[PDB]
Image (cartoon, helix red, strand yellow):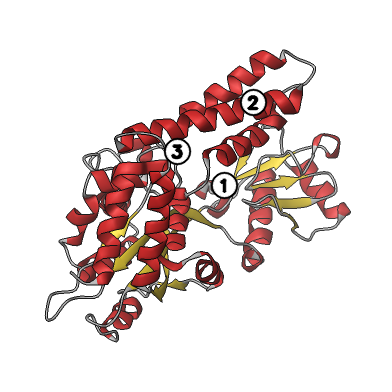
Amino acid sequence: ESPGFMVHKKLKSMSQSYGVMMTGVPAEVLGQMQAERSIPSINKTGNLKQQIAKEVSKVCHMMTEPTQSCGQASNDVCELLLGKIEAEKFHFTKYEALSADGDNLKNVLENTAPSSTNLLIRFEIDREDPPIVLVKTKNENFNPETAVKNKIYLLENKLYFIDKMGNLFNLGPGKKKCTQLFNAIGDSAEYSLCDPFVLEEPEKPEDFAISEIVDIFNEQKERFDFWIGSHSFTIYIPQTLGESPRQFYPYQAYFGSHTLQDWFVSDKDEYLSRIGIDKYIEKLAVLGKTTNTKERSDIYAEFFSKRGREAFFCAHLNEKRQPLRVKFKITEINPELALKNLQETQEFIDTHPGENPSDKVENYRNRAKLAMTEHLESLLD
């Protein structure tokens, strides 16, 4: 077996056995940082001992549930395979959009010697999520720091768009014009920006006001970014031995569904590997090109669901109804460095008391809970 493949075998075996321990963070450090993240949620004029018990329970619940994000798992894979410094450089490298057929990624792989290179690809899937409602609100009741994000807001004297991140965009009209639009619209709580009867066949003055706001917004759409992160994952392509066929392995977590450990325990990496990298890329290109909800949902579920949940993952309420796009970035891996990083993680794990891996994970969890509780009690007196 090639050194590059040993990286995959060891990363998979270690994640299957040790789960959360693979981050390498000492349990006391994790527990203290959990406490400090919980402090802003404790009302200090209230019952302190009861709130602390509540916050500790909430976090320790999450430690036994699928609460690893896809981005966290990708960050861990990249740090283990690249080391901290090079992973930081990888993080600042730009993503490239996958071409409509996937050719740009396919040709990069064809231009690399399968026997001579170890490749790590990081993928990001974005969904297109523009605002869909207009909110009319008096200036007195509008706080841009608290207002719901990804909506257009019409005040007496301002027309705003608050984006996904909470950035506040003045859409242009002056006070006189905003006042006019404000008083031309009725008193409903919200108004749709997508109504095709209102937009194409406007027949009331309110229809014309809303349609004018939509026009104003559409005219400057290149100021905004409507895309938001949907999923993150990595693919590792280790060097081949001799004339052996090149193989790829996808790695991921999916918050609320499964952790990276779950993923490896289910062998969905090996399952998907068997379709071949070319077919995998082709389906990704379809994912980022289709307009069909059913086809988008089916591919998303096939590639990214917890194993065995492919039929439900994107069913009904969870259908993928918005456009998606796929972007990627790629780097070579030094297998000697990756195997050294993995061995140093193994040495950190080996120091935890516990006969079986499951015993060591429980030791880690119990020490993080103790550290969290003592740190919370200390900080609050």
Question: Pointer 1 and pointer 2: residues touching (CB < 8 Å)?
Answer: no
Residue 184 picture quarter: top right
Tell me, yes or no, whether the two marked residues, 2 and 3, touch with CB atoms within 8 Å: no
Q: Quadrant of residue 47?
A: top right
Residue underneath mark 2: 374
The residues tagged by marks 1 and 2 sit, at their Cα atoms, a distance apart of 46 Å
Gap in Å between the C-alphas at discs 1 and 3? 29 Å
| Residue 292 in view of the camera | no
Foreground mark, 1 or 3, reads: 3
**Residue 54 higher or lower than 212, as above or below:** above
Query: Which type of secondary structure does the marked residue at label 3 adopt?
Result: loop
Residue at x 71% of width, y 54% of height: 167
State the residue at coordinates (50%, 67%): 87
Location of the C terminus (image quadrant): top right
Mark 1, residue position:
132
Across and down, in percent, residue 315 comes to 30, 39
In the rendered structure, which amino acid carries the disc numbered 3?
Thr
Residue 13 visible within the image? yes
**Residue closest to the eye, 22 or 207:** 22
